[PDB]
Image (cartoon, rainbow over all chains, first blue to last red; front, side, top):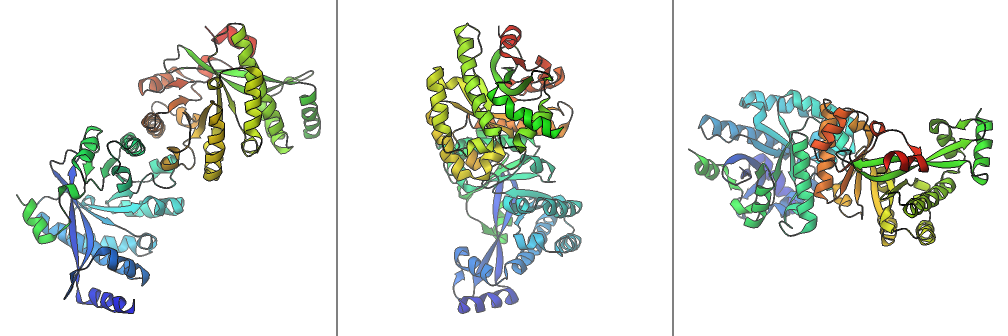
Length: 253
Length: 254
């Protein structure tokens, strides 16, 4: 564990971390709506190290927040670079941890990044799990309002899987609900999943939110989500997360 | 005044001063009766009908809620049998349960006993539980609700979706009905916040194969919104007041 710890300290200072991008599509899977930025790690000898191996130790040593801030900046730089090359990726999505969300420096750091890269602020979408917002609703309301002044978009991740409240969900300045993997995998024949998925979609639409389903791995899941009006979709059905070079080349036109 | 009120309340049970009035429920077009919601009222020999806002929280304070509630449940089932005997077409009766009744180990046996004595179809009895009650201890609730559902009766969640929910555990509860609290109805149709939430409750209910009933429908505009967005059932002052059983059938059942 001190072995892995040493390499991870080394990785952030030597710049061995890299971002890979998962494409997001309209619910018929026909056109690109965005890209989700994911932390990866190019080891010198080992090559690409599995996220399930290095991400948990990162959390265990408190580098999660700091690597996360680097990723946010790199994602925005990347999107800016794509936009200048006329590769119109309408947005980039980045996950925020509870730690980053609660950080007093969050709004200022994001403000700085937006100023340095010059991207349209609505092209940046922060993804926050439901429980982060629901743990402290009044503080979440303060923070989210701050972030929304920057002009960015907010997605609520793992919607419906924990406690929530319709009352506050409507009061949160959010834009998007994400349907977690576990509600997509049983589609289209698993009752529990077809109903909860339908319900998330209808709710998002009732609140003027967009909805995106993650974990779309089969044509049949895609058919269900398409016919029931899910706005966007992502998953292995469309390929794997890829490095910026390859992503940029693929979706250039 | 509270001393005399408490004394009178304590006397009201033995002497049978409590009476049920019923709020009618209709289809979402407001054209057909779908049921009666049973409500605790108090016919005092000197004061007339005592305001629920005055006596009900006193009953809560003095620990008689559950005993009266149990009596109320029995009386509503009896009334439904009386109506059916007289060919008064009230399809079902709904009764609110308090948290203390819900927590009572003997609740299932008591309702079973009432259903047996009255002989009504169990599907004619709908129990209403606030979301708060179910959400405080979702494990216990699951087990209690499972036991109540073995009796054949129906289960409604009111004060959805004020407070905290869990789509995830909502799907697991053996419930049949969601009730839209009046705070989401009052703003209809131009209060965008209420229109959005009311829409979302209707949609969640139908995605989960649940019926949805709106409470506190007080204007035609509210009713028009609800009908047009697919609400299954409605109740409120627009259709008139809670009434005792005889007048209820007279005014609302045909």
